[PDB]
Image 1: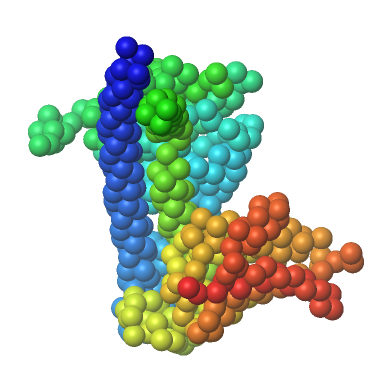
Image 2: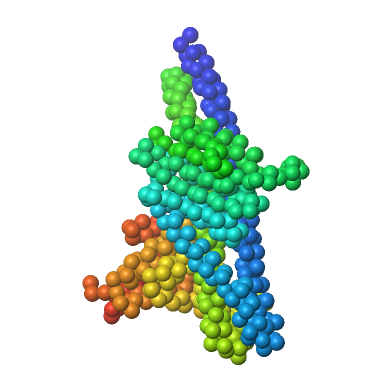
Length: 243
Length: 229
């Protein structure tokens, strides 16, 4: 009958809404887990960076206190000598550090400016030579904040950790832009002394971070990853097309 | 009759509902997670504060290295002794109890806003614009979300700094004032001879945020009162 088809209809629409309502609830739960991962990841990142900066600052203030002995002994010659030999050159290293930081002024993507500055400060305070080159202003990059930040963080963290053993490390950073796309490049000097295997393996961490980096690259068609060794340098390139 | 009526209306209503759940699935699948983005902007504000703390520390350390250098070049052990005792021993000691003293940028206990103002102090220092901070009482909390509080303070100080570039003998004065009823942020700058829309937006979408301007004898005032809840 007619009427019976309606009854039959109301039923199958209620079933349809049931299934949809289960899908919405599942998607809300996935989005909830994602906000939680993002919160804890980034809140831990701030801690580790905060704590590292405080350490650097502690080393600096300690160095000033090595003067105390010369002052207590009223020994200006010994102080003059120690200070000119050991302390006063910091002030030049620090004036140069400040100069290199002006290299990020053309980065007009606020979302990642803090992140890049933090990595440059960390390299500088680890006494790893680092330069950043942004020949033209870059005001737009066509990749979600979270992924772009995670990509940059991994590449710069790899370049920095790989640089801590090396005798004469350098890191070079660049953002360039065609009218087609933006390309993020990090160059670092490869080591000569290769580590022992046991000094490298455990129970971010370079090779892991590179796959979760490949993850992000694969799951965007407009982001092109490249990994190059050229004249004793490791080069990580990520191109993001305005497509 | 009323059965057919109500059945037909039921199929209609369930179609709308199916329509609107279909929309909610699409939004959750395909639109950006605003909450996750806000978490990420809030993370950026903290790392900017950390960066500006370390840049301020470097600028301050360089000045200590300069001061020491001068005492040494002057062969002046007495001066150096008094300076080291009065400024470096305590910096090394770094006593919490010494906090009850500090009345300036040191009284701004909102990590992200202190970092932002440190950025603006350094920016001004580079452009030879003198800048005073008046925070007499400690300021632990402010009743505007970090993102809007940050954008608002930054625009007001950007205004002051841009305005101060044309002038000779410029100055910028910054203050945070806590009543029992509100927090009030004031910025004053010297004037020459005479963006901020995103700012007006924020004050118009906040009942507890009162944005004020004043012209007062060759110096401009910007003021924001944020009432507690």
